[PDB]
Length: 215
Image (tube, rainbow, N blue to C red; front, side, top):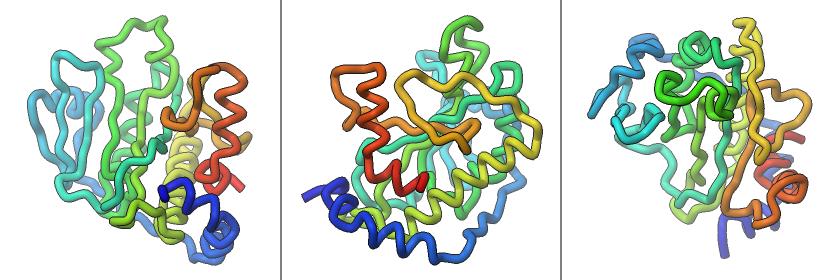
């Protein structure tokens, strides 16, 4: 019994429920830091109910909702966002309304502090944002309405970035994405395996969470 077993046995039901739901609306927040503001979070800062920090021993600014909306145990599902290195601040600002939204399905996320990482390293070239996804229900099963909201949210991120003319970054080797995601990619370290390369990606693509996000 597990998050994935539920997705597998309810694969068509979840998809069918999702595709019939009306468009999600996310009320964007305005009183949020810009990218430099984010970097300056230091030991602790607060914005729109998300706890922020940029500790000296790490290279990401972390954001976590004080009162999480998902009650389930993390099942490994996460998204990266990859944009052109020089465009990370612009991209953060463009997405900040959504990422701090009272309506966001993402309780926890982080953005790389570009100043702390070497310009030629892959960490600078892509995956500068991470979004952690957690099953919404206490029994650690995803509900159809939560899956829909997560998918709508990710697609809103894609449209905001493209509408702002943000240039895509370099997607991590370990991630997968469909042709219509220019910035978003999916990873699950719990289900990817020991083989790396093409084999990890093929395994990711068969993941019901990923198929529900993309088909």
